[PDB]
Length: 136
Length: 133
Length: 154
Length: 160
Image 1 (cartoon, chains in turn green, blue, purple, brown):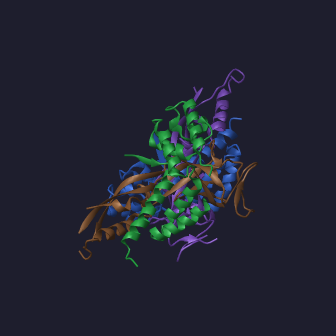
Image 2 (cartoon, each protein chain N blue to C red):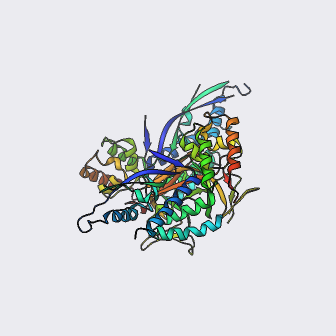
Image 3 (cartoon, one colour):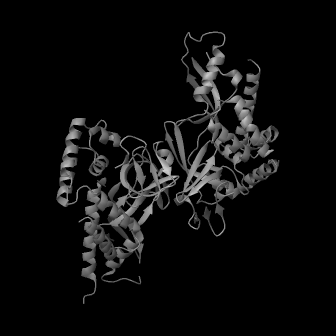
């Protein structure tokens, strides 16, 4: 099926995948703040990646800088909120990434929303997303 | 519908149109040397702005492979008898190519429409019709 | 690519002008509104043709030389400017942008662009492939490349 | 856009048969696909669920990965990493979106005299490190790479 992620989910999903990979590696091996994020990522990548994966490295810093919801709990709340709208995954993903202040802005930036939801409901959603915004 | 032109025909179609306009106005009231005639001609036939037309004529002046109506007419017949699509004909009449592989690589839809052999002859003929002045 | 296309424009003319000269007028206005204009849909309307025969009847019918780039088209042009981002090529009434990423590996920036052979700079003639066209309400943009065989210098 | 996609890869190995050849295969899978890119379906950024990668001479390896692929009309936020007379690049995920000078408001003009290079108007100053919202006007897909061209002309685009 179509699985589109918003930036914050992508961040959690990639980090989790690499943390587990680091663990898998350790088990097999022969025995014997947001700034600390950027540092941790470099270490995580060094330990789990082919060293020359700049695409992934660039992606990680990007996601650390643009992820609006930082913890799984909040992200989980955001996904629940958006799915209960019945919107298409491509719209849910953008809506979960692009912070928007008004219905007009969101509808203008995501034209397919035009006639799938009313301004009032969308306004109510923007408020909820905003309220879930990590203040960290 | 659309009528595709190679660079050389567009150049002639435009000059002719402007020449006729210059007359209609005056009535009812070398490569680089041609470049100088542009400013003049445009001046007497257009608003004064139209930067697009001006850039076009300088372009057509420096890139047109066939400079006189005689030769253009000949290129048209040679290419028209191939049975190729107008868009292909327009490209073959604009882009100078030395080999069949070059042309087929640049105009990929020629691949299964004509043999290397037959396209090589057209290329040789186009090269010999190429203006030298 | 250049084409000759049949077009039409509706011109609103009322009493203030009516007379034995309204045809020459309608024409002057036709040229004013469409010649030198550009649209995403049709391209550049560069030159109205056959002046003495423009069909009036006001819905004015006319023919013109228009230019509109098409994806996959290969064209020759002259380099207008270079930068770390690539170089602009003048093609007809338009500039085609060849980004640094659509230029060969062994060919890179140096400011020009150099290879263990070629040197691309202003006034240089080059063969480019149109990879994409972006049409706005009143303009068109083209991106080109020179990676493939037979593209590039000269 | 970021997606999680079900992908597949056929790998060939009889010199390395063993009780733990499965870890070896997972290793070649990462080398071959992670960090790769095709105009077809984008950047395969990160192979997921390492412990359960499904592996079935040659073996068909079914796995999942976080993938990134831009799309025309998509609006995204990013960071300016460079400016020139031709325009500026915006880092968006693993990709650089190039905004041409012709896809910017006309009042925005290159300041060939500033450092770092920048574009500016009566209000905004766009330069290196600037956060910006752009619209992907076009994607050019090559065999092993994707290119994006963007704009900040429309409403709600530009400096964040």
